[PDB]
Image (spheres, coloured by chain):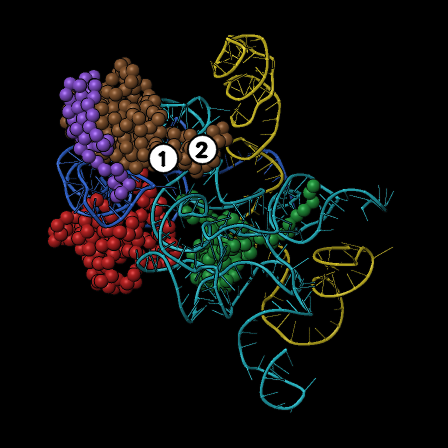
Chain colours: A green, B purple, C red, D brown, E cyan, F blue, G yellow
RNA sequence: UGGGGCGGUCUCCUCCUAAAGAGUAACGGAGGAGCACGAAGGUUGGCUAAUCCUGGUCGGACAUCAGGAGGUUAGUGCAAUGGCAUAAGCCAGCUUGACUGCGAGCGUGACGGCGCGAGCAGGUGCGAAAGCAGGUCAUAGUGAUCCGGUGGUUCUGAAUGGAA
RNA sequence: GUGCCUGGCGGCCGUAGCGCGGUGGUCCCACCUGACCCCAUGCCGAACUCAGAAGUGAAACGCCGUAGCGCCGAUGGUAGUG
RNA sequence: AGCUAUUUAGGUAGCGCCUCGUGAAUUCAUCUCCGGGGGUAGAGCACUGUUUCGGCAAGGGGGUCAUCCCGACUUACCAACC
């Protein structure tokens, strides 16, 4: 017997590439490690990539195994 | 060669029926005389 | 493979330093000739580097690739970096255990003046 | 370690003229030997392993390595990570002492023996033979243990083909029939 | 409650539906939870699979060992999805940060509320040190208010000093 | 004036990586010699580590070709669509 | 004529949607250009299951064995893993 659905976690990307954010602002609320913390960008225990500096969002694909990174340059 | 986990070595001198006495370090307890050897193959 | 295993063993300590933007002192331990390089926070250009491959250091030494060689090298890299003007640096095991020569090279830098 | 020296003198020049190995290091250097004994029946008799562990320490000059279960299997009724194996590995000078113990006091004591078959080479120049007893080694005291625990000893080398390692063994007047 | 008597459902977590931000219904389709661990937690150091090919006492398709290929198809306390070798997987030593007062600034909700969080002050522990640690790979393991019990705290105590 | 080399640390992450043939030892690198002791193995100087270093270039790695593959990859058409 | 909650389901409350007043920044909307992550359509079959088939044919069943046992001439024939 079925008919049960949890909820909607409202996950995904919050701020997109090229946007003026402040420190502490959440960039992407993910579950696994779909993205990876970059420069001046912190990762939470919830894998929630947040900003540590105050600037603009920048998306890239670095590393030898080609993984997505999210960094914020100082503006 | 860790300490106190390896049984001691003693130069063992065992012979053969021909008289093939060989001295090598081993852990036996006694030295017996055998029937065949490398010289008795 | 001793080469590759050493590399993936040093990746964690190496990546953590590059996300810190801290100037590091990377050393290379080999059966002969122990090396040491001071890499800037951009990780592209080095600041200073001394080793026994420079005959000037090994000539006052007995053997190239041992304990006293490490302290002599550690002394050389610390005295040069200070004459260049660098104060705070971070260490680098580089896959090698912080035990002998790696440690020997390390303490020689501290007594000279390199803060770490 | 006299055959260690014998290998480094007579055997090296012996193969440089047959195979013509242009380099000194280009020789089938024997690496290690591992006296293993997949006792396995320790599922109930926990002390069965204790005798076999002491037996390996008695025959070979070192404490053995108690091997667990690499995988859970119900056909033999074992769960992963449980004492079931008893092995050792001689490497270095003490490996030669066992190798000296081999051709002089071990293999001569092989029951019903008139020729050693080297058809148990894995395929990469390494020989992994298995005999049904440890009685060939005089270290066992015959009436001390009520069972002559069989086992399997592997001789690891650096060769490539089987005959490159088979003829390697023949350099010690090894039985071949 | 497809009009009704009958069997299931009700809070919470995962996937699909869901139309490539988020969200999105059905008595639509598969599933699970109402805990567990003092360590499976923190930290420094080391290691990294399954799987078959082959050669081996017992041992043979399926226990142990050696080499090769292979590559994460393994594992990850538990459902599923996302993630993971810089391993979060496996092992060892030392330990208790499973810490206190906060908290820029965001996420998410009508609200109650919930989630993340650099840094600051105090103090602690692992590490040579840089640094790391305010529970556990994440996402379920939970229920408001009132009434009442326990301990602490002169804050109050209807004359005053006390107490209730 | 610079080039040939090796070693280390990076940017860049298969046009970069595999298979294959041939090549490097003065240096350097690797292997290797020895291991009372520092250090170390739930066995083992294998690794970790120290003292060194005869010999070698096999292993390993570096280099030069090879495209037998992987890989990058237009233009045009086609599928789909606002 | 929605969302959330409700002994709630043709009720009600908060929010969205309307209105009037008020105070504010090219504040807001369309278009061009640039900077972004997406994985549905389509394509596709490494992975994930499943597809029927062949083969592999191992697990398995029976005349067949010594038909106490290992084992079998051989094989209906299903067939885990494949």
Q: Callout 1: helix, strand or loop?
A: helix
Quadrant location of the C terminus of chain D?
top left
Q: Is residue G13 left or right of residue E85?
A: right
Q: Callout 2: helix, strand or loop?
A: loop
Query: Which residue lies at the image location 18% right of the left edge and 26% below the top edge?
Result: B14
Vertical relation: C89 (above or below) D94: below
Q: In this view, does C115 lie to the left or right of E4?
A: left
Neighbourhood count class around disc 1 (C-alpha, 10 Å): few under 14, some 14–19, many 20 upward: some
Q: Name the residue under label 1.
A: D50
Query: Which residue lies at the image location 16% right of the left edge and 48% below the top edge?
Result: C64
Front-lying residue, D113 or C14: D113
Label 2 vs label 1: CA separation? 13 Å
Location of residue F72 in the rendering, given as x and y in whole percent from the top left corner:
44, 39
Front-lying residue, F72 or C26: C26
Front-lying residue, F30 or E49: E49
Q: Name the residue under label 2.
A: D44
Sooner in the amino-acid sequence: mark 2 or mark 1: 2
Please say whether residue D28 is visible from this viewpoint: no
Please say whether residue D40 is visible from this viewpoint: yes
Q: Quadrant of residue C115?
A: bottom left
Q: Are marks 2 and 1 in contact (CB under 8 Å)?
A: no
């Amino acid at each position: 017997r079925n008919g049960r659905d949890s909820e909607a976690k409202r996950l995904g990307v919050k701020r997109f590439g090229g946007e003026s954010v402040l420190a502490g602002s959440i960039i992407v609320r993910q579950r696994g490690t779909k993205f990876h913390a970059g420069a001046n960008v912190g990762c939470g225990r919830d894998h929630t990539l947040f900003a540590k500096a105050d600037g603009k969002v920048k998306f890239e694909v670095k590393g030898p195994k080609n993984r997505k990174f999210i960094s914020i340059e100082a503006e | 060669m860790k300490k106190d986990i390896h049984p001691k070595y003693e130069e063992i001198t065992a012979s053969c029926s021909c008289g093939n006495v060989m001295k090598i370090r081993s852990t036996v307890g006694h030295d017996l005389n055998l029937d065949v050897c490398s010289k008795c193959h | 493979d001793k080469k590759s295993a050493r590399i993936r063993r040093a990746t964690r300590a190496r990546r953590k330093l590059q996300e810190l933007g801290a100037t590091r002192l990377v050393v290379h331990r080999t059966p002969r000739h122990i090396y040491a390089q001071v890499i800037a926070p951009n990780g592209s250009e080095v600041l200073v580097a001394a080793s026994t491959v420079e005959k000037a250091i090994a000539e006052q030494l007995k053997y190239t690739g041992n304990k006293d060689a490490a302290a002599a090298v550690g002394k050389a890299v610390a005295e040069r970096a200070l004459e260049k003007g660098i104060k705070d640096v971070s260490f680098d095991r580089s896959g090698f255990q912080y035990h002998g020569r790696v440690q020997a090279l390390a303490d020689a830098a501290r007594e000279a003046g390199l803060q770490f | 370690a006299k055959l260690h020296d014998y290998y480094k003198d007579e055997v090296v020049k012996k193969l440089m003229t047959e195979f013509n190995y242009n380099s000194v290091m280009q020789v089938p250097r024997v690496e290690k030997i591992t006296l293993n004994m997949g006792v396995g029946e320790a599922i109930a008799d926990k002390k069965l392993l204790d005798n076999a562990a002491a037996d390996l320490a008695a025959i070979s000059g070192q404490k053995p390595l108690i091997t667990k279960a690499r995988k859970s299997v119900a056909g033999f009724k074992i769960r992963q990570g449980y004492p079931i194996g008893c092995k050792v590995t001689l490497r270095g000078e003490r490996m030669w002492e066992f190798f000296e113990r081999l051709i002089t006091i071990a293999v001569p004591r092989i029951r019903d023996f008139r020729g050693l078959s080297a058809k148990s080479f894995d395929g990469r120049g390494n020989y992994s033979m298995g005999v049904r007893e440890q009685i060939i080694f005089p270290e066992i005291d015959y009436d001390k243990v009520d069972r002559v625990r069989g086992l399997d000893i592997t001789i690891t080398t650096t060769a490539k083909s089987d005959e490159e390692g088979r003829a390697l063994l023949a350099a010690f007047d090894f039985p071949f029939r």
